[PDB]
Image (cartoon, rainbow over all chains, first blue to last red; front, top):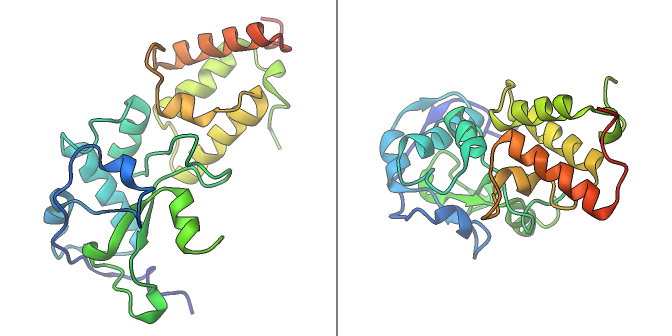
Length: 134
Length: 86
């Protein structure tokens, strides 16, 4: 069966007190967690898929004046159209060029998908690292 | 399909058009623009490719025109085939 990330649900979270340089840290440790500013706006909103979730998150990035600040026009139009910004040449891994949302717990062992405290902003190189090649 | 073979079949105003499209995200999905930027790189040979557009080097002017007048200089410095006959 298709895994339960492409199905409708309610977004839950508190979120982390980040700073504007948050996008550089998505290739540290396990990724940078979702900011409190984006999570406040998504507090029990119904979403129809994870992608539909991802659209909103990225857009709250352009509507929050600190979060899209380090971006240039091309990444800034992206984010304000709901799509993931891209990575530096040390982080784009051939096909995988955009920022991805990834999780601290594996889905299959009880990972809460629509819960923002578990969703980490990752570069390609990091998503690939924890999910071991794939 | 209707793909170009390399940069040496764009005249500069067409390549300019492809970057303008890219730099405003003038399309409907993400999964287009990842393939448009991969086309930009493998056609012009330049190693950094995507990251030139997406994370500006301090000293360069980050707009479609300026990115193309960077590609112009790059090609002629290294001694490459250049664009089509403009």
